[PDB]
């Protein structure tokens, strides 16, 4: 039966482990089964980085109905704007409930989840030559933004 | 648990900029930009239908239209993954309302505990602890993660 709307639930089959989300935490070591869940992929991929996991998922999706299930759902989330691609390394990033800001696990770029784009310009933190420019001229990057760092 | 925050919903009118924050006791969003009523349980605009009629009509349209079937097959995935459930009383598909651990069904008005994916109460409604998740009975939450299932 899982857990709260505020929680991530472990992906080990039938595991009762769960956690809350935190802006600067992208992995969850389940205290029940001890497997490391990646919160951006919503998957356990302990032998791979996220790009390797997602490229392998697309490969398995050609001859596996359950992987094809997963990938075609991601395609719809991407189109609906529920997920996004990292603007730097282009992995698929899925939402962490209540987090307006994400640091990519693969390339470490800061992502403004509210606007579905980079937080900063190419110079990184403090570079408002690009990115969402939250609170430049006092204006939030979107009226719904509470804290995109 | 987590730092209390507000969770946004975006209007389903194509390319509309309207948006709102989710609230426990609000299941409909009247967009202030386009004035269309969004149902926050179906995540769709179905102003001439109740939610059961909308979901039944969507399943019908799935057999011939491409977009309707990717919508319905996504819901079936969401059901197995646990990002959605069926109302324990009237059995419509209920999608997660971000930041809400309690939901009052739009069709039958049954209170739903999202945390346990089931009824909040027994058959007698509020206060009936003969069924439901029994949250806070003897000071014990219905699940350690529960943030407020009323
Ligand atoms: Zn686990
Ligand atoms: Zn990952
Ligand atoms: Zn990246
Ligand atoms: Zn931002
Ligand atoms: Zn912002
Ligand atoms: Zn609108
Ligand atoms: Zn509805
Ligand atoms: Zn119902
Ligand atoms: Zn409950
Ligand atoms: Zn509860």
Image: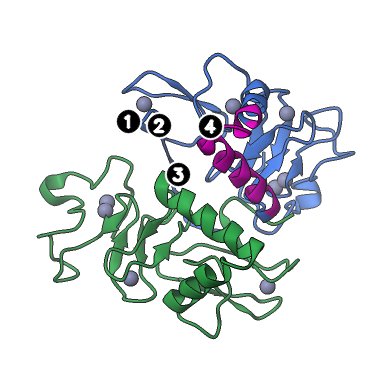
Chain colours: A green, B blue
| Residue range (magenta) | B59-80
Chain ID, mark 3: B
Mark 4 CB near ligand 7 (8 Å cut): yes
Which residue was labeled with disc 3? B7
Which residue was labeled with disc 1? B16
**Within the magenta stretch, is there residue B72?**
yes
Residue B121 left/right relative to A6: right
Sequence-first disc among 3 and 4: 3
The secondary element bearing badge 1 is classed as: loop
Chain ID, mark 1: B
Sequence-first disc among 3 and 1: 3
Q: Residues at badges 3 and 4 in contact (C-beta under 8 Å)? A: no
- Residue situated in front as seen by the camera: B65 or B75: B65
Residue A112 lies, in percent from the top left, at 30, 57
Residue A119, picture quadrant: bottom left
Say yes or no: labels 2 and 1 on the same chain.
yes
Q: Residues at badges 3 and 2 in contact (C-beta under 8 Å)? A: no
- Residue situated in front as seen by the camera: B67 or B138: B67
Residue A53 left/right relative to B128: left
- Residue situated in front as seen by the camera: B88 or A135: B88
Residue A85 lies, in percent from the top left, at 36, 61
Residue B131, picture quadrant: top right
Which residue was labeled with disc 2? B11
Residue B40 - label: 4
Distance between the alpha carbons at the discs numbered 2 and 1: 6 Å
Q: Is residue A81 visible?
A: no
Which of discs 3 and 2 lies nearer the camera? The answer is 2
């Amino acid at each position: 039966p899982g857990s709260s709307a505020f929680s991530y639930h472990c992906k080990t089959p039938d595991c009762k482990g769960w956690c809350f989300f935190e802006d600067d935490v992208n992995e969850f070591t389940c205290p029940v089964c001890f497997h490391v869940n990646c919160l951006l992929c919503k998957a356990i991929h302990e032998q791979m980085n996220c790009k390797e996991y997602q490229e392998d998922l697309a490969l398995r999706a050609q001859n596996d109905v359950a992987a094809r299930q997963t990938t075609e759902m991601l395609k719809v989330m991407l189109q609906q704007g529920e997920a996004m691609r990292c603007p730097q390394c282009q992995i698929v990033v899925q939402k962490k409930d209540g987090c307006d800001w994400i640091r990519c696990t693969v390339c470490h770029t800061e992502i403004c989840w509210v606007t579905k784009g980079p937080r900063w310009g190419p110079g990184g933190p403090g570079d408002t030559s690009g990115g969402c420019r939250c609170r430049v001229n006092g204006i939030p990057c979107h009226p719904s933004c509470q804290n995109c760092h």
